[PDB]
Amino acid sequence: MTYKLILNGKTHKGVLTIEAVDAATAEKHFKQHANDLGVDGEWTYDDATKTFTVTE
Amino acid sequence: MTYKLILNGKTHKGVLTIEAVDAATAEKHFKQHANDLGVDGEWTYDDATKTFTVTE
Ligand SMILES: [Cl-]
Ligand SMILES: [Cl-]
Ligand SMILES: [Cl-]
Ligand SMILES: [Cl-]
Ligand SMILES: [Cl-]
Ligand SMILES: [Cl-]
Ligand code: NA
Ligand code: NA
Ligand code: NA
Ligand code: NA
Ligand SMILES: [Zn+2]
Ligand SMILES: [Zn+2]
Ligand SMILES: [Zn+2]
Ligand SMILES: [Zn+2]
Image 1 (spheres, each protein chain N blue to C red):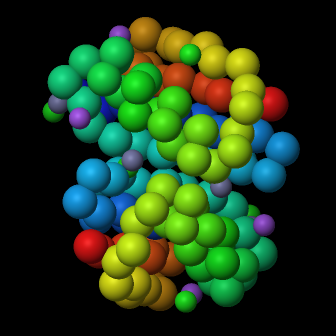
Image 2 (tube, protein in one colour):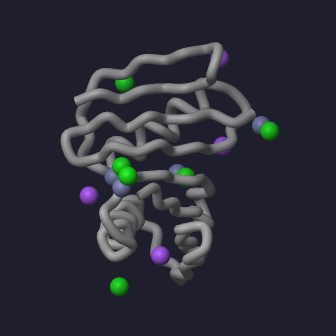
């Protein structure tokens, strides 16, 4: 299914959408993106919208 | 305005949307994302949809 990441970082404000087999796979991918971007924030997940938020 | 990046990398297939004052500013931001993700691809731009694509 489609999963989304809302980036709410100091220098990264955006929305990323990907496809993944499950939420765990999406979250692993999203955490790698955030790590590569130097985003070090607090994570939340909304199951109803399959949307993660990372907030610095 | 809103600008989009279609990631068509070997390991990064996704869509990123951001806001930016102009296409040049969006593209600079997008190129930094792609650099941070280790995406080394060919860039194209569609003015009508304010959408870049990076293709490995
Ligand atoms: Cl699907
Ligand atoms: Cl961003
Ligand atoms: Cl973690
Ligand atoms: Cl705007
Ligand atoms: Cl991606
Ligand atoms: Cl360049
Ligand atoms: Na996957
Ligand atoms: Na879920
Ligand atoms: Na900007
Ligand atoms: Na344009
Ligand atoms: Zn799927
Ligand atoms: Zn960004
Ligand atoms: Zn704008
Ligand atoms: Zn990716």
